[PDB]
Length: 13
Image (cartoon, rainbow, N blue to C red; front, side):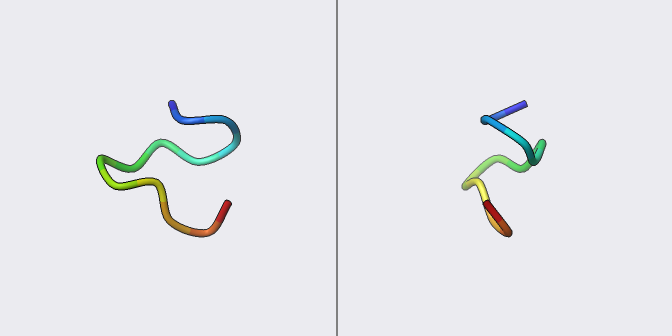
């Protein structure tokens, strides 16, 4: 994903 979360804009990380 991003680092921990797999969002397009990276949220909750």
